[PDB]
Image: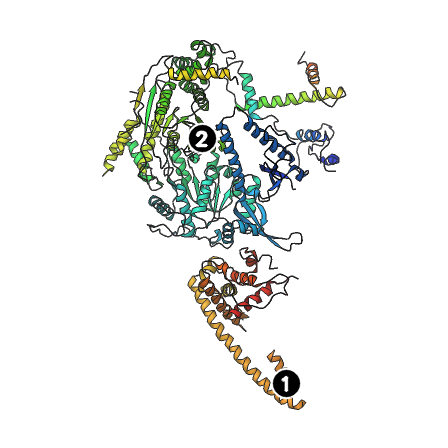
């Protein structure tokens, strides 16, 4: 018994839009934040709540970006998102402008 | 209740329910035998065709018809493993596992066999791990424990007894339902242990109710009989007496014996004494580390085989299997469930994971092994175990105090909460008499609660261990790195690094790294190589860096050359695994057979390296350890010298590190070389270490298990020693009242062998090394209730005089005296004979009068003849129980005594070899089952073992092999079995 391609994706869409947990693991995000922070200056300490707030900010920004990207892909008569959809979204938002 | 505020905004209503149902997606959603494990392969598929075509490599389709694979199927028991073929399988689930097995193992094995650059060492280690995998999989065939039995109906197979079997190294989620017959024919000892485990003498529900009324304990000078095991030693016997005396006073304790003395045997024997002697056979819990838990399981299997010790590990389903198949005698009930097991072995992780499922159990004893893990009162394990409802606790450890007195305060608060308080810390700078009075008060307060035996007090054959502290001068690179870190020089610390990402957080950690080796820092080997090796980086200069970058590496190289000159083996302990990588590369380019153990190595390769180093034909010379890894179970008997490269803050870690090689039975004199850097941060590390050692020698060592006048002087002397710093034929493998012996192992010996850059790798070493580099380029590469209960025991066993202790402690009798139950059984047996003879006397005279009337009526016909035919064609009351079988009570008493005397006279060694001989009973060919003379002896054997009328116990006993010959429209039944038992005993008697 194999599933049709697309109903599993719809199940994950309906599942992950209900729950509110963080979809990125804590330790790779902490390592990424420390690597990004250490070029501005060395010897930076981080509170746990600071990295958590950065995490939910990244969550909200990237989820809103994928909503705009999905709208760009649907507007181009597609169901698959592409990097051209992402660069359109950020351009119209003014990030690439 | 009602809201006092509303909204005047005219919004539409919104359904906020975010609960979704996937019932609109069932059109693409919904609208157990397969390959699980592949174990072994054989080169011959069906028959040996020939020895030709042994060259080249086979393909995937070539191996599909050439090899047969051993298959353990899904939901099987590792005994139905089948030798199958790809064409013999067809298409089942798990074919990808077989493909991965065939591909990976066959391709890599023929690649390592057919390659020309594979040495003999690689081929022998792959053969050794192949044999390890083979016998590890072969160990799964042996059963280890039988959980439960059931009666299941097969496909027209009537009823079959079916055991729940646990295997040797498998867990309870691999416990399988199997036939009883091959389990009996395979391992009958576990079947007999299971048969003992149903009607066991010891239950949690039969425990005593000692509420501050425990009996006095007399000292045992001999090993107790219920501890079978091997033999108990004298110090273990005194520890047993100490534990029993502490429990008799209702006190908790710490067994602070040194490792190797057999603390596990002591606590197993104490658990056996608590269960057997004091009748405290309730639920006990023992919490152990996971690595030592097989070493506890085999100890319980050996020394206390009659105990119901269970194991609690694994995933959720295995723990659920243990919970609802083994915890309770009555798991199907809903009221109060009493326990079935006696001892529960578990670990810390499942104490924290299952504190809800284990905290609601009235435990009678807790035994926590390795109590230093419990040294912190703030940790989750402390609050998890402290919330348990346990009357008596015991802590087993080797080091009770490690850092300060607050840890020992946490242990004594976990033992008994409140009469012992510690609120004042110790200060060596004070050194007043009040501190000595406090120390002596702490000595006399915890003296009977801590039992400590050293390895220098028992087993008078252990060679002495002498540790030497060596101080060395730093190199120029180490000195400039120390100056750059201590006087922070981020721009100078960056220098030539392209990234320049230097972190100076944890200054002391960077100072320790600079004291160890400059190559721990990033982009540091390049600066040494360009300024000394002239930028060529051709091998011999790089190792020339590795000895002269750090001031400890010259002493380590000299020590390795000196120990290679002699016949000795060396362990190297380090706190950092990156330093272990540095020494591993140093011995790799150096060319010394080394083995390694750290946290990244899995336990299988750890066991492989330990067995490889301890083999008598081992070519390994140096064995590297991370200091805080491996637990207390590492065996390193073959090594002789221990070198501590990095000194730990906790000295007990260093004592465990040097006791890795200083175990019981060491045949060589063990020396420890502690590598110390001069005028660096490691000096205060050793100052804190010697302060903690002084503290442990003060409290712990002087409170083990006319001198009190000199105690006030020698405590002052040891506090004056603890208040002073130590910093104001060197590597000899030789060494030539206890107060001045602790003044040893603390002196510092300096080392100033200043050797230049080129004076290492001499002409003997350089000629072989340059030849290897040149050759590399060429090759490229008594009420009424007791009366009825005793009446049921008469029909089961018979006489209750010799089986009074059997029925009372098994629940067949109430809580009464043994003499009162014995006197009631003798009075009922004597009164049954007189009541039987009273009814038989009147019945004999009744038939005489009826026969006289029939003779008078016979002449009238030529009625009373029917009266004589009705009479021709035994109940009493003993203690309120009416309709008691007085005739059957005396008949069953004589038949059971005759059966027990006949079996013990000729078949005392083996009761299963009983034979009827030349006695031929009546045929039973009319029954539905094939009953013969062999089946008659099996039923009579079970009568003397399980009792008369126990049809469930006789049918479940698979030793007789009559499980399928008894049905309980089928014949014989329960009534037919009772009639055949009485007819067989009456015919023999």
Q: Earlier in the sequence, mark 2 or mark 1?
A: 2
Q: Residue at x 47, y 33 (%)?
A: B607
Q: Residue at x 31, y 20 (%)?
A: B750
Expressed as whole percent of the image width and height from the top left, the position of residue B808 reads: 47, 59
Q: Is residue B752 above or below residue B304?
A: above
As drawn, the label of residue B349 is none
- Number of numbered discs: 2
Secondary structure state at the residue bearing disc 2 = loop
Q: Are marks 2 and 1 on the same chain?
A: yes
The label number, if any, that marks residue B629 in the structure image = 2
User: Which chain is indicated by disc 1?
Assistant: B
Residue B591 located left or right of residue B30: left
Residue B496: x %, y % from top left: 48, 9
Mark 2, chain letter? B
For residue B739, what is the image quadrant? top left
- Distance CA(mark 2)–CA(mark 1): 101 Å
Residue B429 to residue B179: above or below: above
Depth check: A9 or B334 in front?
Answer: A9
Where's residue B102, x and y in %? Answer: 61, 33
């Amino acid at each position: 018994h194999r599933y049709r391609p697309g109903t599993v994706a719809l199940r994950e869409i309906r599942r992950y839009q209900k729950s509110t947990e963080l979809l990125i693991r804590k330790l790779p995000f902490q390592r990424l934040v420390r690597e990004i922070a250490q070029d501005f200056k060395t010897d930076l300490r981080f509170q746990s709540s600071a990295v958590m707030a950065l995490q939910e900010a990244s969550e909200a920004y990237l989820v809103a970006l994928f909503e705009d990207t999905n709208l760009c892909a649907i507007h181009a008569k597609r169901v698959t998102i592409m990097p051209k959809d992402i660069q359109l979204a950020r351009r119209i938002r003014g990030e690439r402008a | 209740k009602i809201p006092t505020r509303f909204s005047n905004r005219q919004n539409k209503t919104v359904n906020y329910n975010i609960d979704y149902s996937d019932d609109d997606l069932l059109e693409s959603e919904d609208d157990f035998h397969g390959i699980d494990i592949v174990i072994n392969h054989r080169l011959k598929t069906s028959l040996e065709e020939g020895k030709v075509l042994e060259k080249t490599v086979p393909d995937l389709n070539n191996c599909k018809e050439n090899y047969e694979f051993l298959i353990k199927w899904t939901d099987e028991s590792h005994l139905h493993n089948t030798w199958e073929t790809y064409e013999s399988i067809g298409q089942v689930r798990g074919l990808k596992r077989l493909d991965n097995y065939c591909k990976q193992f066959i391709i890599e094995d023929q690649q390592v066999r057919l390659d020309p650059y594979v040495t003999a060492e690689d081929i022998e280690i792959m053969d050794m791990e192949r044999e390890r995998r083979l016998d590890e999989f072969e160990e799964f065939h042996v059963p280890e424990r039988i959980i439960d039995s059931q009666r299941a109906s097969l496909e027209d197979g009537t009823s079959q007894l079916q055991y729940l079997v646990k295997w040797r190294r498998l867990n309870y989620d691999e416990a399988t339902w199997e036939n009883a017959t091959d389990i009996v024919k395979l391992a009958p000892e576990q079947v007999k242990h299971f048969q003992n485990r149903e009607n066991s003498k010891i239950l949690p529900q039969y425990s005593s109710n000692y509420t501050s009324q425990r009996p006095r304990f007399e000292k045992l000078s001999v090993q107790p009989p219920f501890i079978k095991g091997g033999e108990l030693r004298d110090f273990q016997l005194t520890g047993i007496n100490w534990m029993a005396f502490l429990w008799s006073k209702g006190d908790n304790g710490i067994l602070a014996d040194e490792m190797g003395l057999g603390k596990t045997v002591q606590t197993v024997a104490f658990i056996s004494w608590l269960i057997f002697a004091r009748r405290q056979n309730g639920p006990h819990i023992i919490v152990v580390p996971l690595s030592t838990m097989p070493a506890w399981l085999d100890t319980f299997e050996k020394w206390a085989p009659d105990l119901n010790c269970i194991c609690y590990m694994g995933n959720q389903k295995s723990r659920d299997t243990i919970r609802e198949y083994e915890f309770y005698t009555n798991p199907r009930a809903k009221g109060k469930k009493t326990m079935k097991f006696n001892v529960l072995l578990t670990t810390y992780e499942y104490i924290l994971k299952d504190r809800a499922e284990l905290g609601s159990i009235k435990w009678q004893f807790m035994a926590v092994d390795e109590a230093h893990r419990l040294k912190n009162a703030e940790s989750s394990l402390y609050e998890s175990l402290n919330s348990f409802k346990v009357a008596n606790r015991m802590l087993i450890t080797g080091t009770p105090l490690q850092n300060n007195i607050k840890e020992l305060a946490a242990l004594v608060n976990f033992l008994m909460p409140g009469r012992f308080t510690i609120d004042q810390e110790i200060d060596f700078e004070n050194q007043d008499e009040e501190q000595e009075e406090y120390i002596h008060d702490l000595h006399r307060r915890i003296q009977p609660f801590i039992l400590r035996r050293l390895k220098k007090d028992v087993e008078k054959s252990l060679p002495s261990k002498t540790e030497r502290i060596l101080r060395v001068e730093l190199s120029d690179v180490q000195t400039e790195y120390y100056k750059n870190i201590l006087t922070k020089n981020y721009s100078a610390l960056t220098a030539g690094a392209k990234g320049g990402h230097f972190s100076l957080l944890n200054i002391m950690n960077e100072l320790k790294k600079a004291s160890n080796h400059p190559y721990l820092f990033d982009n540091a080997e390049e600066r040494v190589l360009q300024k000394f090796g002239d930028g060529k980086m051709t091998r011999e200069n790089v190792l020339r860096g590795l000895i002269m970058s750090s001031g400890k590496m010259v002493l380590l190289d000299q020590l390795l050359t000196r120990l290679k000159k002699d016949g000795h083996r060396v362990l190297i302990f380090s706190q950092m695994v990156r330093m272990l990588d540095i020494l591993g590369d140093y011995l790799s380019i150096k060319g010394i057979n080394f083995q390694r153990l750290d946290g990244t190595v899995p336990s299988a390769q750890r066991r492989i390296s330990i067995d490889h180093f301890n083999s008598p034909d081992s070519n390994d010379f140096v064995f590297l350890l991370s200091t805080r890894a491996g637990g207390l179970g590492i065996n390193l008997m073959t090594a002789d010298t221990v070198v501590i490269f990095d000194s730990d803050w906790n000295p007990q870690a260093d004592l465990q590190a040097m006791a890795r090689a200083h175990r019981i039975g060491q045949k060589n004199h063990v020396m420890v070389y502690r590598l110390v850097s001069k005028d660096t941060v490691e000096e205060e590390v050793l100052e804190r270490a010697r302060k903690k050692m002084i503290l442990e020698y003060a409290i712990i060592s002087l409170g083990v298990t006319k001198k009190n006048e000199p105690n006030a002087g020698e405590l002052s002397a040891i506090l004056k020693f603890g208040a002073g710093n130590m910093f104001t034929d060197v590597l000899n493998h030789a060494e030539d009242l206890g107060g001045e012996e602790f003044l040893k192992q603390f002196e510092v010996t300096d080392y100033k062998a200043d050797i230049d850059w080129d004076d290492i790798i001499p002409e003997e070493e350089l000629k072989k090394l340059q030849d290897e580099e040149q050759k590399r380029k060429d090759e490229e590469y008594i009420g009424e209730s007791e009366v009825r209960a005793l009446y049921k025991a008469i029909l089961k066993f018979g006489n209750l005089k010799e089986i009074l202790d059997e029925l009372i402690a098994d629940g067949t009798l109430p809580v009464k005296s043994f003499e009162k139950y014995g006197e009631t059984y003798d009075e009922m047996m004597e009164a049954a004979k007189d009541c039987v003879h009273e009814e038989e006397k009147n019945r004999k005279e009744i038939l005489e009068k009826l026969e006289k009337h029939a003779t008078a009526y016979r002449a009238k016909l030529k009625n009373p003849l029917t009266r004589l035919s009705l009479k021709k064609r035994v109940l009493f009351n003993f203690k309120g129980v009416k309709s008691l079988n007085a005739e059957s009570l005396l008949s069953r008493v004589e038949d059971l005594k005759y059966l027990k005397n006949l079996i013990n006279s000729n078949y005392k060694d083996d009761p299963l070899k009983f034979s009827l001989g030349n006695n031929t009973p009546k045929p039973v060919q009319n029954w539905s089952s094939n009953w013969t003379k062999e089946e008659d002896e099996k039923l009579l054997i079970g009568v003397f073992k399980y009792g008369y009328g126990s049809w469930t116990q006789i049918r479940d006993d698979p030793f007789l092999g009559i499980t399928d010959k008894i049905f309980l429209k089928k014949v014989p039944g329960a009534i037919h079995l009772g009639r055949r038992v009485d007819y067989l005993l009456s015919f023999l008697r």
